[PDB]
Length: 337
Ligand SMILES: C#CCOC[C@H]1O[C@@H](n2cnc3c(N)ncnc32)[C@H](O)[C@@H]1O
Image 1 (cartoon, rainbow, N blue to C red):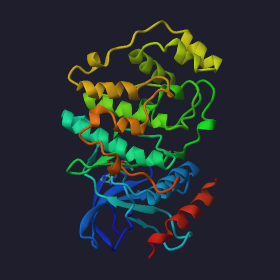
Image 2: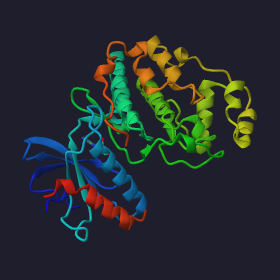
Image 3: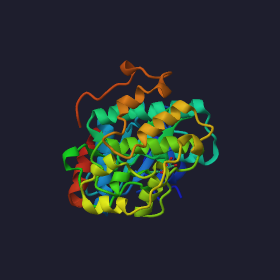
Image 4: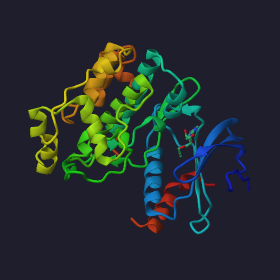
């Protein structure tokens, strides 16, 4: 069995391995697909020793196998042992992508043309996800893969859920898992993140980051995240406060000194004015006034690309660690032998 840096037990179909980077649950390599005569990406996942790892693994596999969209990464193949007792790892094979938006923003200035194209592809993929009544819940630059000609594909649905807006309300300072800098303000106030507006906020943060190569709200701890957001948007209006019925949440906002909005064109003086109009509508404080994905696609900033007949939707809407391993075994059976 081939070894890298750790057994990489993917033969014989896949050979000529090359380390790419560490992942949540193991190694990511490129490898030559001796069947399709192309290099692919392979992710080694060793999750069976922790329930939370098994949850994220089953979610990714189940959703990505059901989804088929040009802007969403596919699963080409899954490698594991023939029996549950012998299965200690799972290998997910995907198209090989050159980079991701996180690594790209580290070193590359984006032209306005690239920003517009990236944002269109993000929203086009998100239209399909939301059409299936699914929330991604962890959109951020490192979960946006790019190939050598700047085709973009959303990946990592490990925290994704079915939308559940009737159960979205919670108390003030409720704990949350998804990446801090991309959390909507209502997560810190009264929301579990069970509605589609949680994803639009993240896309808004991603657009701001594309405009300046710096995360717009780099909060350093839970509550600091909310105070970063308020420092740019300014104090919420009386109407937006009155939508927050929870008293601990509302009284915290009331306790803060008045802060004025920072104009987007001051924060991003080189930005296209239409880009900043859309940014404003995505980074709206009140989640019920925040723009939806299909409205965002129809915004003048994206008029070069907008074609709703070429922006498809899904055909239909979409635990102990021992038990999750069983379901992972069964979900991956279609790729055997
Ligand atoms: C798991 C995980 C996240 O970090 C994974 C490393 O794998 C990378 N990566 C993940 N999927 C692919 C992929 N499909 N093609 C190329 N590189 C990839 C990611 O950009 C990073 O370099």
